[PDB]
Image (cartoon, rainbow over all chains, first blue to last red; front, side, top):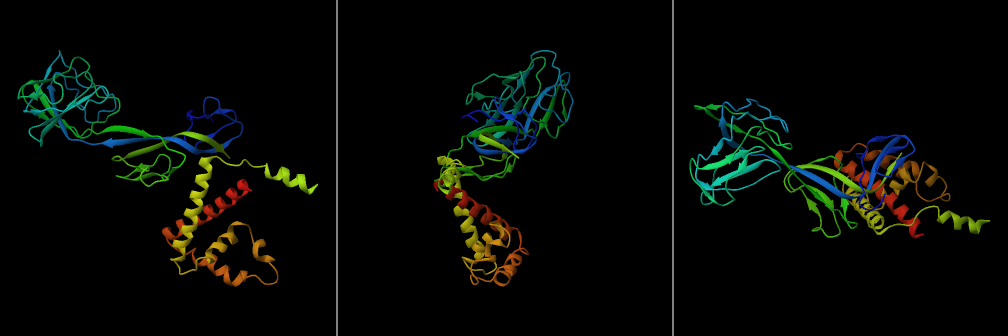
Length: 226
Length: 114
C-alpha cells in the first residue's frame, strides 16, 4: 500500500477473494487481516456539559433523546433566543450548532445551547445583558448531526418554554504517527484521561489522550491477511 | 550446489525499512526486560526463563534433545519452570507473552542483517 492511502476495511475484519481493502488493493484469499505500520490514528473524544435553553411551546418538538439530527421544535417564525443573564459570551461553535458560555469576571453564570440554524447575535467576548437578544432560530432549527441530547428537562412559562439538556458531543482529533513511534493501544479502544497512545523514540514525542474518547487506526503502511 | 544454495536462501526474505528496524529493536528490548521483570516474579534467574523461552518457542523437545550427552537437564531444570509460571496472575503472564514475541523479533532482525 502506497504512502497516505487508507484502508476501506476495518482492522481485524474478515475479507473475501478479490474484495477491496483499499482503492487498488485486492485480497485473493478468504480470511482475517491486520494493520501493519499505520501512519495515522483518529481519536474522537467525547465532551459532556449541562446547558439550559428556551423556545416557544408552539415550537418544542417534545422529545427526550434527540438523536444526531433528530428534528428539533417547530417555531412559527424567527424567535429570538433571549438572554436570561449578563456576562461575556463564548462562541464555541461546533459544526452547524453553536454554544454560548455566559461568565461575568471569571466564573460562568450559565451555558446555553444553540441547535442548527440558530445563529449567534454577538461575537465572543462581547457583553450581553438580561433579555438581550442572543440567538435566532427559524423553521427547522434541528439538532446537530454529531451530537446527542440526554436527560430532557421540563419548565413551562407562558408561550416560551424552558428546557435543559445534558447533551454531550464529540470532539475528534487525529494524530500522524512516525517511524520512530509505535502504537500502545488496540484498534477501536476506549481511552481514559491521559492514556498512552503511541510510544516514541523520545518519551515526549509520544501521544496521550486529550480528554477521553475512541481510537481509530488508519493509513496503514500495509495490511496482511491470513 | 551448497553455495548458490545459501545465495538464494538469504534473498528469500526482504531486508527491512527504518520503521521495521526500530520496531524490531523495540519489541526485542521490551521482551528481554519483560524477562527481567519476570525474573523478579517467581524468583527465577535472569538467563533461566530466557532459554526456557527458547524451549517453548524454537520448537518441541528437539532443542535440548541432543546438545551433546551433557548440556543442561530438560525434564528437571526446564519442565517444572514451564509449569511454575503457568499458575500466575495477569501481570506475570503478559510479561511472559512479551518475552515470547520479543525473542522472535530478535530472530527476524538477525535474518535481515544476515
